[PDB]
Image (tube, rainbow over all chains, first blue to last red; front, top):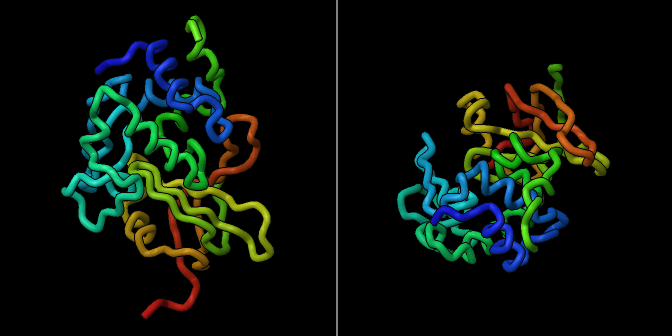
Length: 129
Length: 89
């Protein structure tokens, strides 16, 4: 599913991301935009054998289980297909654990490279929430 | 600007393309993030990231930069990582 910007904004607010750990909703929409172009089905295989799955590109080494990466912890306790659905619940619940890990949103290259320090609330501009 | 920092490992995080080691000075306080990024960090460092565990003493060489945004600290992009403390059996 390829979310609309405002659609996802609403979807993320309803799932409790706004100000979660002090990151306002614009951050989360902004990360989705650059991690996965909003595509819930986005997957990306890294040269080390891990894969990043879903709208927030959660990595398979520590965070979910996809069977095809050695010595893998499954800290989010879910299969990596659960992250490829239209229902972003699983992705969101896993993002919560990640962002609580001690590094906030620094867990995400795309957020780091393209959203951090910017006018992130621009990403909820024009949204009816 | 290249730089050398030293201290103990406060936390390790593996997020796939980004791996973060937080290095802390003897008497606590700030803990500086060191970022290993798959596009950019030299290959061998990943191997040593996988050897690191909490409270290990490291000497890290790398580039220091100011963090983006108003949360106004510093970030380090390593070119070498050395482990100082007694080796595990």
